Image 1: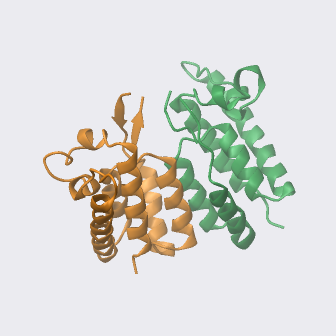
Image 2: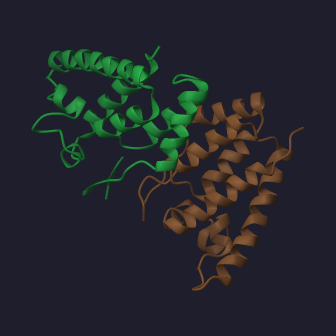
Length: 134
Length: 135
């Protein structure tokens, strides 16, 4: 997660939290009330960049579950970019920022400068993607 | 939880607290389910004593809550003995670990707690939670 001291600083997830979450997904399922409670609290209790989401997902999910998450992340990005382009005025956030990739957004330091609207879009897209894991 | 390390505070969502209360109702405070969920939350967020109080009070029956608080205080008493006896001494007292008194009763004060104190609070409260008995 990113903290805004404004000066943005990145702090990695707790190793124990990650271990807890991987074991919880395994025992209860990625969308059990168990995981929904935990994940929602983390997502809304922190400023998460795409890097954070990639870490949470890759660490917590089985390989097949992770593939599902990524496809739905990409699906949510398609829809979001469409809404961004159609907004009046257009919202200048594209897929590179929402996925955390490319020359402008691939590094943690770049992503840490993401504005509120972008953070909110990433949060909604990734929570939806997680919820769509079957 | 505290949203900026030493600083400000954001409450748990009403929904999250409802889920925790339902989880305790369905599975009990010391199900592996609740134990690992609590552990996850406690390592996923920076919890001050005020958070622990809200979580416990919201999730537990009055008698379970009294047990939790009794064991939190007991664990604090043991931790303070250890802090005093440490070489060098750890300058963390019972009022900080419990979030009480002139120095620590407010969220604004608690939000300035450093890592060692947050960690001590976490260990003590997780242990106290485990000491709660079922109906």
